[PDB]
Image: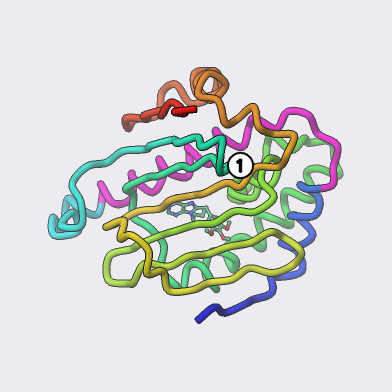
Amino acid sequence: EVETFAFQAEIAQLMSLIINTFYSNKEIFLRELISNASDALDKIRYESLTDPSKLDSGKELKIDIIPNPQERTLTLVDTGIGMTKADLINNLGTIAKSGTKAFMEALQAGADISMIGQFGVGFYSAYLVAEKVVVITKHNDDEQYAWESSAGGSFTVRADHGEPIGRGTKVILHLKEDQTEYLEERRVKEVVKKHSQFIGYPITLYLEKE
Ligand SMILES: C/C=C/Cn1c(Cc2cc(OC)c(OC)c(OC)c2)nc2c(N)ncnc21
């Protein structure tokens, strides 16, 4: 059963700005999504020190980046803490409102879009290159969910009965037609080396088969 929700007006405004503003330095999306994965990995690692059972859902802490030219998708998979249903519908957005406001104000005062991560809303930089984002996520003590948005003011959340991911998050970027450069491991490697070379988890960059 698919439930459809409206973004808060401010977040919809932010998404529209990211989609409609002329800004050529789009590659920064990858640094932001990798940093989100790293943060999530940091969180489950820290929690596991006082409750080792939190790793019963998977011991390995890693990030995989998988380009699929045929599906026109770039997928970032982490085995971090994951997100709950409450995160997806309510709590991440509640937190994001103030960061969104501060970022929008910063842009008006001369900041550029590449500073988005400092405001906690770097996730939304995905829409620099993606027409649709699907997030499959699994947190301990909650079910696996699929979140989806093609912007336009709404997102959906549904229980996901696809392949279990155990714990963590799969961010599936359905790329815009003119952003297919990010479907080549060569380009992805260049971006990772430039912006994400010191991330403290193994990042495996898959090669496209075709
Ligand atoms: C500061 C927000 C952290 C939530 N988060 C995001 C970014 C993110 C995902 C989101 O939903 C999937 C968000 O709400 C739509 C959101 O709003 C700022 C941010 N990636 C991940 C991830 N890989 N693993 C665990 N949590 C994550």
**SS for dot 1:** helix
Residue 152, image quadrant:
bottom right
> x%, y% of residue 1?
50, 81
Q: Residue at x 49, y 49 (%)?
A: 171
* Secondary structure character of the magenta stretch overall: helix
Q: Which residue is drawn at 22% across and 42% down?
A: 60
Range shown magenta = 20-46
Horizontal arrangement in the rendering, residue 91 relative to residue 164 (left or right) = right
Three-letter amino acid code at disc 1?
Answer: Gln
> x%, y% of residue 137?
41, 60
Give the residue at mark 1. Answer: 118
Q: Residue at x 56, y 44 (%)?
A: 71
Q: Is residue 104 above or below residue 6?
A: above
Residue 122, image quadrant:
top right
> x%, y% of residue 156?
59, 71
Residue 35 located within the stretch drawn in magenta: yes
Q: Which residue is drawn at 47% across and 68% down?
A: 87
